[PDB]
């Protein structure tokens, strides 16, 4: 009975390999778009990151020249 | 069975990269939420 | 009287523009803090 329950549980056991071929092809496609989307995601995250860095630098300069203003 | 091995490797790296991606937006969103909370806190202290 | 004056430095210090100078430095640091916090509020809202 483990033989029976393993032989029938093979995904693709009752699925013809050619629709696996299309599903795999479209999987690499949507993969291409998902790393693309990650490219825009990371570039705008870095953009906001160095906006934050610029405001950090401006605030630090303000602190420095304020506490040395007296 | 070579195609099946290709499939299984396919889903394992796909789910791994989805996990990495999702933790990336989770962490950046939590950092942004912390920044907004700090901004509100400093505005209240003004 | 003179003994009590002698042991306490604080009273002898108590015993006039410096206060105005301290007020000016406090208000200028307060206003620069307000300005930088306004800048942070404006920048972070994007």
Image (spheres, coloured by chain):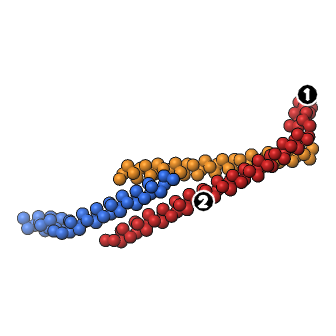
Chain colours: A red, B orange, C blue
Left or right: B43 as drawn, with respect to A55: left
Residue denoted by label 2: A46
- Give the residue furthest to the left: C1
- At x 35%, y 62%, the residue is C32
- At x 52%, y 48%, the residue is B33
Cα gap from disc 2 to disc 1, whole angstroms: 56 Å
Residue B19 visible (yes or no): yes
Q: Which mark is residue A35?
A: none
Q: In the picture, residue C11 is in which quadrant?
A: bottom left
Residue A6 visible (yes or no): no
B2 or A51, nearer to the observer = A51
C33 or C16, nearer to the observer = C33
Q: Residues within 10 Å of mark 2 (few under 14, many from 20)?
A: few
Say if A10 sits above or below A65 in the image.
above
A3 or A35, nearer to the observer = A35
Q: Position of residue C39 (x, y in %)?
A: 43, 59
> The N terminus of chain C appears in which quarter of the rendering?
bottom left
Q: In the picture, residue A20 is in which quadrant?
A: top right
Left or right: A10 as drawn, with respect to C39: right
Residue under mark 2: which chain is it in? Answer: A
């Amino acid at each position: 009975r483990q033989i029976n329950k393993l032989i029938d549980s093979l995904p693709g056991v009752d699925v013809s390999a050619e629709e696996q071929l299309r599903k795999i092809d479209m999987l690499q496609k949507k993969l291409v778009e998902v790393e693309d989307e990650k490219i825009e995601a990371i570039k705008k995250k870095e953009k906001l990151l160095r906006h934050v860095d610029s405001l950090i630098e401006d605030f630090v300069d303000g602190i420095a020249n304020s506490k040395k203003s007296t | 069975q070579s195609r099946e091995s290709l499939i299984m490797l396919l889903e394992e790296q796909l789910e791994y990269k989805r996990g990495e991606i999702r933790e990336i937006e989770q962490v950046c969103k939590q950092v942004h939420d912390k920044l907004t909370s700090i901004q509100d806190t400093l505005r209240t202290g003004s | 009287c003179k003994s009590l004056i002698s042991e306490n430095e604080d009273t002898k210090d108590l015993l006039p523009s410096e206060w105005q100078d301290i007020i000016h430095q406090r208000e200028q640091e307060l206003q620069i803090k307000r300005d930088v916090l306004d800048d942070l509020y404006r920048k972070l809202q994007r």
